[PDB]
Image (cartoon, coloured by chain):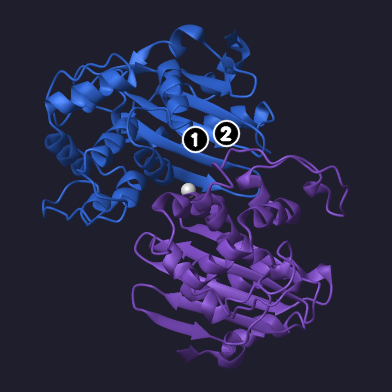
Chain colours: A blue, B purple
Amino acid sequence: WQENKSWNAHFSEHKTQGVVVLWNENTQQGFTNDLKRANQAFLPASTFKIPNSLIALDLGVVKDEHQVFKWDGQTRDIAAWNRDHDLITAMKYSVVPVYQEFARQIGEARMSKMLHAFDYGNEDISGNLDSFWLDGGIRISATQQIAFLRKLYHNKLHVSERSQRIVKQAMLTEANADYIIRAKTGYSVRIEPKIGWWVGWIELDDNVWFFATNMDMPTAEGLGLRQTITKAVLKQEKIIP
Amino acid sequence: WQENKSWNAHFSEHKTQGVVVLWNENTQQGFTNDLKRANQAFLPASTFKIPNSLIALDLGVVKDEHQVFKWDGQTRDIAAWNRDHDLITAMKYSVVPVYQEFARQIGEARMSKMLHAFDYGNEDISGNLDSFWLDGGIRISATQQIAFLRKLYHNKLHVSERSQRIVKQAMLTEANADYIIRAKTGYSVRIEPKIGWWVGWIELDDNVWFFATNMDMPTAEGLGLRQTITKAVLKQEKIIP
Ligand SMILES: [Cl-]
């Protein structure tokens, strides 16, 4: 691994602190601004919708990316959540209640078994079955997110190939003539320290760069920095124009 | 079907002529600027890379989207062709020689059978096996492109679900927070009349709009118009911002 303490400027410039981790697939070399925070584990929050989606698809809890999950009629604080969703829009708008019902149907035994097979973080689901990724005992670091994401990219996780392709479709975030981004955001607010996440990868013509970013997030006002800081580093390193 | 002549403004501004065809999947209604040209058949040229990809994958000529197809060492006029490619970059850069080798390995009997199964245009492959979509007997209209693409979107073509998801991945062209475009360009120059194509669809949160465009292309100078004129119509109908 390679440490560049100069990169810390991107976080301090915004009066916060955090970590960016990059991985070059062709050369098999990793880069970060801070090796210790790169290996520090946090609640995954909505980045857990990647493994949760995979498990639900493989077990038949979700039939495909078109199946409609009806609003239960309870008015919640996020307007985007108070409507019907399929897998694509539930990912895009990070619809917590849809995923809470997934976890209930998967069950404790099958959830635990899958995460052990995935080698996902500390593999620990202690807490409520329907909120453990929000205020329970599961933890994962930026470097661990990278390792998990590399297996998904190569279809190496122990679920069907079909499941892995459908989730990668649902992760699609941005695309143009120069690159494709597949990724997922997160915001952990229930337990200190509050942090924001962005994890995923960038597909180029002849290479792939994996990334995992997190940063302290005392208020929701700074959530855009999740993407902004990551893109600033990528542009800096000439990965994107 | 419904005719909207106001769209002609977008063509005449550039002193050229053509057709745009749109299909609203939610309501099952079609729209076009020229009912007559919408049904006129042309060579598919590089839009034929969609069915050619599906067939190559389903028969194992292509193992997956990562398999590398080596350059044959002949320097052709388009520099981007003179190098190694996989399925994703061969679609992106319209690499004719890679697909000419696909066709040779598929063979006449299996190609023909697949096109009958797909209801693809006039289903006629007469000519050279390695160039019939460029200067042989196959023909397809803008309206027939729509029908074929609808089958693909719904995984209804007579190949595996997997083959269909991989080609849809390879068609990925643009994506942002407002929409996703999966499509393929074409440029028919060997046989008159010279034309340009852009065929595919736009994915929204709650609907999908299919599109098929062609226009006269006496010179390469106007190739950028395939996308800009299509985009102009979409903007007018408030489908994209
Ligand atoms: Cl995709």
Q: Secondary structure at mark 1?
A: helix
**Would you say A215 lies left or right of A73 here?**
right
**Would you say B202 lies left or right of A43 here?**
right
Residue A227: mark = 1
Q: State which quarter of the image contains the N terminus of chain B.
A: bottom left
Name the residue that disc number 2 marks. Answer: A231
Q: Residues within 10 Å of mark 1 (few under 14, many from 20)?
A: some
**Would you say A161 lies left or right of B71 here?**
left
Relative to A197, say whether A205 is above or below. below
Quarter of image, res B10: bottom right
Residue B206 on image: x %, y %: 34, 63
Q: Chain of mark 2?
A: A
Q: Is residue B236 visible?
A: no
In the image, B101 versus B64, the foreground residue is B101
Does ligand 1 reach within 8 Å of label 2's beta carbon? no
Kind of residue sitting beneath label 2 = Lys
Residue A180: mark = none
Please tell me if label 2 and label 1 are on a single chain: yes
Q: Chain of mark 1?
A: A
Q: Which residue shows up at 65% across the image and 49% down it?
A: A177
